[PDB]
Image 1 (cartoon, chains in turn orange, purple):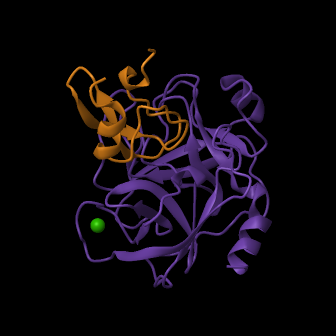
Image 2 (cartoon, chains in turn red, cyan):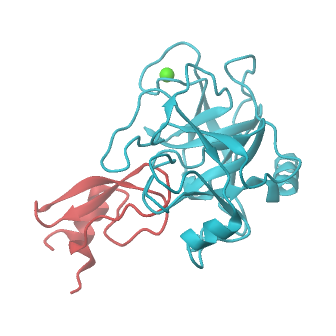
Image 3 (cartoon, helix red, strand yellow):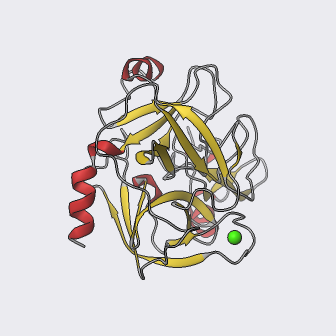
Length: 58
Length: 223
Ligand SMILES: [Ca+2]
């Protein structure tokens, strides 16, 4: 609190189309989103496992 | 690419797709063994796809070659985005002919107003998401450093330049990063970043390749 796991996914200004995971507290699961490649916020993971380990239950 | 048009099969022979299980960035072939892309496109296990048009279907002109080296500029700053350039060496030399060719590096920097060709398989919508199957093209002018700095206060370095239309509607977008900005047959820019896509008063920002020619040539020659 402010729990970074509750922040909306952040694509950022860069123009890549990299698939990353973010914890969706509304749905209670780790979902995929497009990350631009730079200035990532913390609710951004390289795998569902990393996302669940860090944010599961948020 | 937002507000662009279908390039046409292999009409941009130096355009490559960087694949890590899916397309995530573009790149420019400058030598049979080297590709120029953006530093923020760095990933391990990159596979370079040349001769591509429809990135979702095998059409018969593709060459899939793994990256043997992915060298990010030593001064790349992941916060300011300064020096957003990366050189990728191909594990095996690419076969060049007509649908796959290299693009020349600049001999001098381009001036504001110069019309260039920007291409990629990135998002085609400014509001929403729509990723194309085939390569998209866009003609856009290089903008003055003054207008670029006005659009992005305290964010434009000497190694960046803006290109596009201030009215909005035409721009590079997510999925185009690392891709080419070619002006008069020379690779002048690398798709880098921007505020959203094709937004009014927010033109795309590109890595100023002309500032890295000596570094590129020497790095490629020493690897
Ligand atoms: Ca294909």
